Image (cartoon, coloured by chain):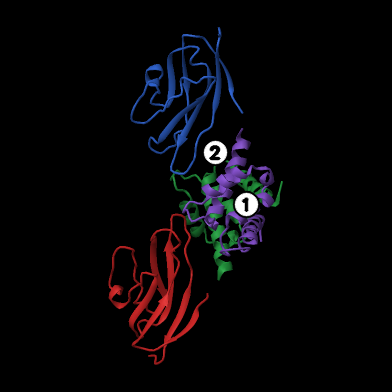
Chain colours: A green, B purple, C blue, D red
Amino acid sequence: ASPLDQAIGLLVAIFHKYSGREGDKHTLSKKELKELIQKELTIGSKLQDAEIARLMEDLDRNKDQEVNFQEYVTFLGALALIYNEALKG
Amino acid sequence: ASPLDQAIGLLVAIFHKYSGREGDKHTLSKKELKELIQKELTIGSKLQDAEIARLMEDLDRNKDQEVNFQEYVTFLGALALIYNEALKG
Amino acid sequence: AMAQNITARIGEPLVLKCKGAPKKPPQRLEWKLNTGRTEAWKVLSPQGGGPWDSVARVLPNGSLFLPAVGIQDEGIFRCQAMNRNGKETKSNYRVRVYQIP
Amino acid sequence: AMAQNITARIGEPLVLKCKGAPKKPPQRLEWKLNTGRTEAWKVLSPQGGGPWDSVARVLPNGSLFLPAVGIQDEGIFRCQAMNRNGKETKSNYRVRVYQIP
């Protein structure tokens, strides 16, 4: 696969690395998502517990206490906007 | 940076690699986007010209003939859905 | 493509459970099935009914019962749901009757 | 943080052009500015006016003219737009008057 397909494939692989551990196999629990953030995000381990909790709460749009794949894409989009804004000044 | 931040950073870098070549520096023209697809997408070079044109047309939601960064994220989301659906069977 | 092998008899009643609706209130739901000609695919709603309603109904527990499964019922059935984001349930069950055309 | 250095005189009229609206029809628009106390930030709409409307208006070409820029006008001005996706324009201009408090 090409560099772009490989990067996307890596990001999808990360999701499933954690989503299948407990509860629903294809969604992220509060526990799984916090773990994903703390281990996969550069600044994840340094965030306040209250701020991770607010982050996870907001990602959940359908309000079922579960972060599906589409919610994870919202997170990726937020990260992309952050890096893009920094580069513009 | 961590694996996830690195992958996102790579994807953002690809966008700007092509967006700055002509016209607006921060958006993808029809020419830039077609080039991005043909060079960065595994199957890009094998797609019909008509299908690339339809793809680029649809990505443009605000209808200004320019594919901004938010439109590129829609493309990434579409790629992620494709790989995810294949894995589920 | 995944499908469960289930044997059935023509004109014989059959009941099945198709869960999916989360712990939240009754959300939206859509019925879809893939077959050769497809003549059973109907749109299910939490407030309303259609033609297939007379052919088969859904139990309050989210089940499905048919007065008599015939050749028209043959094929593969699939369940699906629609939330506020895009969390849908995927499942296909292959059903075939004894005597076929 | 980026800002343009522009000199101005208190009570002196000033005109500036703040483009952003694409080739499409008149879309939405929002006015925002960062200052110490901030007392000029107003919400601009394609169909309506407010208090700042009397302090400054926007030309059909998407410009801005002030009858007399004073200390209250000081600070940094910024333009912004809202489309169907999220294509906004970022630009901050630093403006200061001769005599200051």
Can you name the residue that lies furthest to the right here?
A1
The quarter of the displayed image where residue D16 is located: bottom left
In the image, residue C82 lies at what x, y percent?
45, 37
Q: Which mark is residue A55?
A: none
Q: Under tag 2, what secondary structure?
A: loop
Q: Residues within 10 Å of mark 2 (few under 14, many from 20)?
A: few
- Residue drawn at the location 48% of the way across and 51% of the way down: B61
In the image, residue A22 lies at what x, y percent?
57, 41
To which residue does mark 1 refer? Answer: B34
The three-letter amino acid code for the residue at tag 1 is: Lys
* Front of the two marks 2 and 1: 1
The quarter of the displayed image where residue B21 is located: bottom right
Q: Which mark is residue A24?
A: 2
In the image, residue A28 lies at what x, y percent?
54, 45
Q: Is residue C101 left or right of residue B63?
A: right
For the residue pair A25 and C4, the one nearer the viewer reads as C4
- What's the distance in space between the residues labelled 2 and 1, CA to CA? 39 Å
For the residue pair C59 and A48, the one nearer the viewer reads as C59
User: Could you tell me if residue A30 is visible in this image?
Assistant: no
For the residue pair A37 and B63, the one nearer the viewer reads as B63
Check the residue under mark 1 and report the chain it is in.
Answer: B
Q: Under tag 1, what secondary structure?
A: helix
The quarter of the displayed image where residue D32 is located: bottom left
- Residue drawn at the location 69% of the way across and 49% of the way down: A6
- Residue drawn at the location 55% of the way across and 7% of the way down: C99
Is C15 located above or below residue A79 in the figure?
above
Q: How many marks?
A: 2
In the image, residue B11 lies at what x, y percent?
63, 56
